[PDB]
Image (tube, rainbow over all chains, first blue to last red):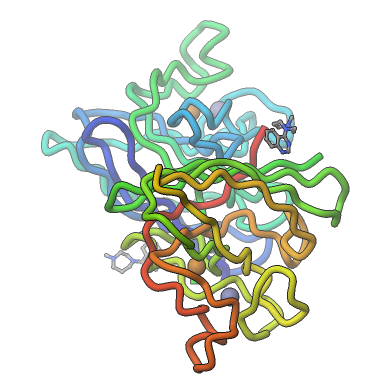
Length: 153
Length: 153
Ligand SMILES: CN1CCCN(c2ncnc3ccccc23)CC1
Ligand SMILES: CN1CCCN(c2ncnc3ccccc23)CC1
Ligand SMILES: [Cu+2]
Ligand SMILES: [Cu+2]
Ligand SMILES: [Zn+2]
Ligand SMILES: [Zn+2]
């Protein structure tokens, strides 16, 4: 298998740890971990293009989009490679994450390693919000925490 | 050109920013930036194998060594791919870095993107210290600051 990992930090209380594992080349990637310090509800969760956090999470640029598509949800055909939807926090501010995604990869042109995982301020509307920004960012707002996705042992 | 970047942080006062640029595929890589908060003297400077900072800089593992060689300096034929020698701080605590290396790459099997850059506690002896550890780590001590090397715009 191929493995990757991301430590999420920002300027506020949000922080987390997310693991990625891919059994086979071109097969699905399991994504799991925990994020804390959140407000209750949905927070957009995306791989952004650049693994640059020079100036904070803003430096990571737009959602990772090697296939030239519009923004969507992870269950949509029309989506960015980096569109992993939302994580959902309870009242305690914790999101336990355990999903599988077929579009991200840990090798090749869909590879997310060396890019930035970001957890956002607000819900991602998954492109269904009825404005142009919806089909670009999902209207998920600012970047609460992020980290560069790295190769794991 | 291909570009990458790394934000160095840790538990202490050391922090920095390092840029990488590779003009031609498989060509030399320019490495430049600044590290502050260092004690006066040499600090070992390496790409480590993993981009895992789960538990801090320790999680990055040994030096990036795809060819299973012994530790050396950047000028040596016998070196780890990640062996970038030392950065050198004055009394101001600053090392202003400007290196070119032809062994590291931002593509291929020697790609450093997705791995961890680390600045160490003390001098790297470039494998000339006369003990087994010299030939593994350069006796450069603990990990003051690190970050995952990411794809840049
Ligand atoms: C509760 N935990 C302990 C075992 C580590 N965990 C996993 N390990 C390996 N692969 C996974 C794939 C999908 C979801 C979780 C895991 C689960 C976290
Ligand atoms: C457009 N680019 C990134 C920053 C500017 N560039 C540099 N390249 C290489 N070394 C440097 C050392 C100090 C300051 C700037 C650079 C040229 C490539
Ligand atoms: Cu996003
Ligand atoms: Cu090192
Ligand atoms: Zn998107
Ligand atoms: Zn080494």
